[PDB]
Image 1: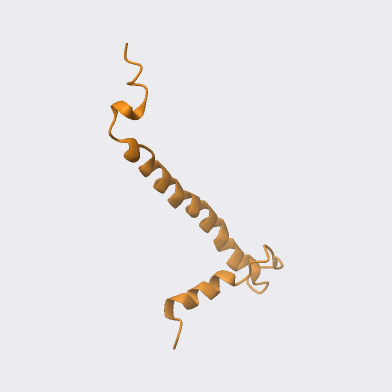
Image 2: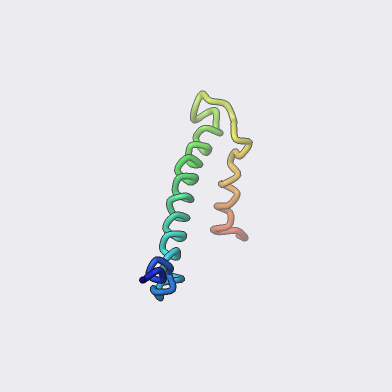
Length: 72
């Protein structure tokens, strides 16, 4: 019989089997969170939208932009 074929042992792609799957999912997962997150920026500013602050996040992500230039 060939019961080993069922297991990854027969394949040397032991690490490459889940690899692509995990990283790909992280991009899209970050993707979904990121997409919805953008709404927080517009939803936070009452001036931009009638909606009132929410998620308690606010211009929190904006603080990260500082990370781009940081010190003068």
